[PDB]
Amino acid sequence: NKFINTMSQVPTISQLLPLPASDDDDLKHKSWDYLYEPDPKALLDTLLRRYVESQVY
Amino acid sequence: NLNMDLLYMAAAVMMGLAAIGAAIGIGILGGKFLEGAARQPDLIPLLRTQFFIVMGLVDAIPMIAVGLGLYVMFAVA
């Protein structure tokens, strides 16, 4: 359920995997690109796992 | 006579080693420059100033060598 208001709430079903195509657009990443320690893809996997955990919470 | 035959050889060896030294020195120094410019576009004008500041000292001795090579070749002859 979603706590839309103090007075009203609604039941919902939302897809958490695969990652939804949220807009999430910026191009400022050119100015600050992360130095991936140890690897970029390893960090990305841990980030996705944390994100799913966070959305469930 | 023999003098000029060896003096062209002397100038040759000196400027050849100078060429290798200077060229590979600036090659490495510039390689770090380009990689440092790669990731972030912000400070190209900044690194390209530190580049000349250091590149001056790279060329310090090789132009002593070149000056003396030219000196041998055109004035000791």
Image (cartoon, coloured by chain):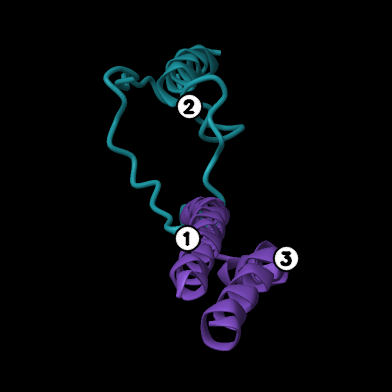
Residues flagged by tags 3 and 1 on a common chain: yes
Quadrant position of residue A54: top right
Q: Indicate left or right for A9 with A18 as reference.
A: right
Q: Which mark is residue B16?
A: 1
Q: Secondary structure at mark 3?
A: helix
Depth check: A6 or B61 in front? B61
Quarter occupied by residue A57: top right
Q: Chain A, which colour?
A: cyan
- Residue B52, given in percent of the width and then of the height, sits at 65, 72
Q: Which shade of the palette goes to chain B? A: purple
Q: Nearer the viewer, mark 2 or mark 1?
A: 1
Q: Nearer the viewer, residue B13 or B77?
A: B77
Instruction: Identify the secondary structure beneath mark 2.
Output: loop
In front of the other: B51 or A26: B51
From the top left corner, tell me how far across and down residue A41 is, in percent: 40, 21
The subunit carrying tag 2 is A
Q: Circle 3 sits on which residue? A: B57
